[PDB]
Image (cartoon, coloured by chain):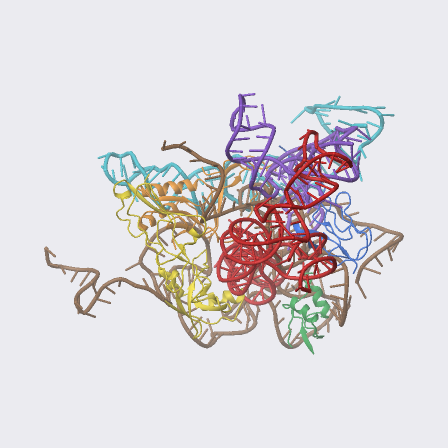
Chain colours: A green, B orange, C blue, D yellow, E brown, F purple, G cyan, H red
Amino acid sequence: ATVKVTLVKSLNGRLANHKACVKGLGLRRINHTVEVQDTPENRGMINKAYYLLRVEG
Amino acid sequence: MLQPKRTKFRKQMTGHNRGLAHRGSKVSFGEYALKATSRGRLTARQIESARRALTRHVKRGGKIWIRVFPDKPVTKKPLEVRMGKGKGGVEYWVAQIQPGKVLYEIEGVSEELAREAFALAAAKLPLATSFVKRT
Amino acid sequence: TRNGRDSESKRLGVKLFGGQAVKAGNILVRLRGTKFHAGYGVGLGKDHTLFAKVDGVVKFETKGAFGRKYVSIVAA
Amino acid sequence: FIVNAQVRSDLGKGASRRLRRNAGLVPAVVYGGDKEPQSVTLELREIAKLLENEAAFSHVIALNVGGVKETVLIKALQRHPAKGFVMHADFLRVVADHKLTAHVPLHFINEEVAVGVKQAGGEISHTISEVEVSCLPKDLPEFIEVDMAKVELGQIVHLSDLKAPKGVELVQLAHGNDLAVANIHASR
RNA sequence: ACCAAACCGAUGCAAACUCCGAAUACCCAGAAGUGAGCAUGGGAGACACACGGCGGGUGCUAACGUCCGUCGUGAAAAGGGAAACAACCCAGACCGCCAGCUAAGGUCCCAAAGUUGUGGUUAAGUGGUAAACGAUGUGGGAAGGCUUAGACAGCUA
RNA sequence: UCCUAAAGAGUAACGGAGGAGUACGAAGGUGCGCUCAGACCGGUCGGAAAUCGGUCGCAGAGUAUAAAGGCAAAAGCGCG
RNA sequence: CUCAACGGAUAAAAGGUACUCCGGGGAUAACAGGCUGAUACCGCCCAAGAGUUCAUAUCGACGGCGGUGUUUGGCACCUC
RNA sequence: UUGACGAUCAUAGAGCGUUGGAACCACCUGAUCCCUUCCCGAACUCAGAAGUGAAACGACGCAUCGCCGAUGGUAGUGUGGGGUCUCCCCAUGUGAGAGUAGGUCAUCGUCAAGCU
C-alpha cells in the first residue's frame, strides 16, 4: 500500500544530499503531505531524512 | 635524563592524545603500582623528581621499575623572533600519558609504606594518579 | 638547511574498475612497477603500463602461487 | 562459589551499554565443548564477591542460567581500564573428559627464614606468578606451594625445581623452555 | 668483581615503520517514483575573502594568529531568539487584513503567556565566573570492623 | 622521490627530509646456461676477516646513478 | 641561448637623495588602544634539607597549579 | 600398483616415524663414437645393462612448529543532537584487530598404465 509523509523541518540549512532526498519524494514546503508508493526505494529515502519527516502512517 | 641514544629523525609532528590505554594498564612486575587517571604529557624532568622521591622514602630495599619512556622531541622558538622562519630547536623530551597507564611499580615493601611513598611521587607529577594492586 | 622542492604529482592510479567495458587501447592502470601483473588479455607496456588488446569486461583476480594480482579481461 | 544468570536476547553496542548504566548488569557468554555458545547477563554486585575471592580463578563455579545448572570455570576478564571494574565475563563449560587449561596462583610459603636471608644480607624477588595448569577437571589445583627458605644467596629458582602434584603437567616444560621463578640477591 | 653482543621469556612506542584493517568517499552497471544533461555561439562579472563546525601543519595543541581539506552561513537575507550581538540557533519577505495554528525561546513584575501538578535535592544568594589542593558540609549506595560474655566515651589506679 | 595529503585523482606554508644539469657501441638485441648475503666447522706464511671444502640458508644480497614502488618466464650473474 | 629571474622584456644596463617631488594605502611599519601571556610581577601546593637538637620562628633545593595586565614580546582588527 | 600434464595456492607447509620394487623410476657401468667442461663425463650428452631401493622419490602415520579460526565483548566511524567543549556522551546505522573454544598430516581433472 501507501504511506503518508509530512515535512516538519525546513530545507535551508541542510546538506546538498538530504535536500535532494526530500525533493525526490515530492515535498515542496513545510506541512505538505504526499502519498508515496511504499517500495524498497522510496522508504530508503525516508531513512536518510528521518528527522525532517513525520511518517504518520 | 631519559632520551634515546640515536634517532632516525630530528623533529616530529604534534598529533593528538586520544583514546584510553588497554595495553599498559596491567601491573606486571611489582605488586603495587601508581596508574594514571587523567590524560597529559610528562616532560622527563618530572620523572627524575618523582624517581628521586621514591628512592629515599624506602632507604632499605625494594625494586623500582619505570614503565614509561619519553621519546617525543618538542621544540620551542627563542624569544624576540617573528613567526615563520623554520622550526625551533629541540629543548626537551616528552612521554604521552592516557587514562589507565601505569607509571611506577614497587615490590618488596609494605603496602602502607608504599602507599605513603607514592603520595610523595604524585605531588611532583601533573596528573591525577591512583593506587592499584596486583591480580 | 632549507628545504622546499617537491615534484609535480604524476597522476598515477587505477582506471576502469570491476565491471567496465573496454576497447583495444584503454589503459586500465598506470602503475609504478607491477602492483598488478599482466593477466589473460592485457599488455604490460614499457614502464609497466597495462593496456587492453581485446574487448570485454575487467576482472581483477588473485591467482597462483606468490599470490599475485592478475588483471584479465573476460569476453563477457 | 555460586552465581545465577539470565538470558540476554539483545545484542549490540547500544543495548550492551544500556545494561551497565540502567540496570547495573554485566554481559557474559557460556561457550563449551558439547553445545553452542550462549550469552548471559550477570550483576556487577555479585561478580564483585567472586573476583574478591582468592582461589576463585582456578576453581569450579556452578552457574544458574535459568534453572539450568552447569559447572563453569572462568577463563577471561575484560575489565574497564580507566576506572577499574568488571566488563563482560567470558567463561567456560566443563566437560568430564577434555583436558583443560587455566592459571594458578603461587604462594612462596616459607620465606621468613632463608639461608640467603639470615646468613647473608638477603632479598627475595618474586619474578613470576600466575603459572598455568594442564590438568584433568576432576581434581583441581587451587595453588602451588613453593619454598625458598632453603639454599642460597645467589641462586635462581627454575620451573623444574617446583613440583606439580598428583600428575599435573606444566605447559612451559611442554614447550622447550624453563622460566626462572624467584631469585635471592644482595640489596643496594 | 668488567661489562657486554647474540639467543630465550615477559614488557612499551613512531608523520617520513607494516603480518593486518573498517566506516565513509569514489567509479560502472539495475531498475521504480519525483524534478534542466551535453555541444556550438553572443555578453559579462570574478581572480583582497570573512567566521563557524569537523579532520590537520605551524605556534605555547596561545591569539577575532597564519597556511590547507570539506560542509554551512555572511558577502548578496530581512523577520523571531541570545539584555544590546553580519558569520551562533529558528526561518527564507509579491501585495492587503483590528483573522487562526506553530518553530527555536519561554510563562512572579518591568514584558505577551502556569505564583500549574508530582517526587526529591541545595542555605551558599550556590544558582548568577576558575586550578592544583584542603575539610566530622550534607543526600544516596554497597562494605566491612567490634558489641548486653558489657564495645566505644567518658570518671575512676 | 618520500612525508604533510583526510584508504580514487588533486591540494598550501621562508613546513619536515634528500637528489639531478649525466653515463654506456655494451652497461643495447637474442639464444643458451647459473644463483644471494650472511652463520658457522676444516684448512700452508693472511687470519676478527682474502682463496679452497663443506653443511645451514629460504633475498636479510644485487639493481651504472637519490629515495620510493618492484623483481624465479628472475628486471640479478656469465658466455656465443 | 644559463639574465639557472630556468613560459625566456633588448644584440647590448650599476648606485645615491637628510635638497627632494606627484599619485595612492591603515591591502602595510614606528606612538597610543585591542586580542594573547611565552616573559614578567604576586601567590599557592609537596618538603630534601639548615635553623647546635628540632622541615614549617625564619628560609626551603628538586618539581607542580594559578592570578594581575605592570615590561621584553607575538599578531596586524581601528586611524596615513 | 606408477608415470606425464594440469586445477587450487599452507586447513595443501616443515619436522619426526614407517615403507615401496624388478613393471615404472632412480642411482649405476663406460666414453669408443655424438657432445661437453674460462680445469674436471660433476653438470651437459651418447651407447647400456648387470647391481641396488642405500641415497633420492612416492605412499602411510604423528598437531610437536607453522597455518587457518569461531561466538561474545571492545576500539574506531556516517547522519541527527548534547555537555564540565586541547576530550567525551545520547539516539540510530555500521562494526574490526588482538586474544579464546577449537581446527588442519589437503581436494580434484586428463591420458598412458597396475584388480583396474
Q: Position of residue F25 (x, y in %)?
A: 79, 28
Image height of E128 relative to A21, above or below: above
Q: Position of residue B56 (x, y in %)?
A: 33, 41
Q: Position of residue F8 (x, y in %)?
A: 69, 51
Image height of H40 relative to B24, above or below: above
**Could you tell me if residue C6 is visible in this image?**
no
Q: How many marks?
A: 0
| Quarter of the rendering containing residue D4 | bottom left
Residue for point 42% across, 64% down: D73
In the visual, does B54 lie left or right of A39?
left
- Residue at the limit of the structure toward the bottom, as seen here: A1
Image height of E79 relative to F36, above or below: below
Q: Position of residue G37 (x, y in %)?
A: 50, 43
| Quadrant, the N terminus of chain B | top left
Residue F69 versus residue E88: which sits nearer the camera? F69
Residue E79 versus residue A6: which sits nearer the camera? A6
| Quarter of the rendering containing residue H48 | top right
| Quadrant, the C terminus of chain B | bottom left
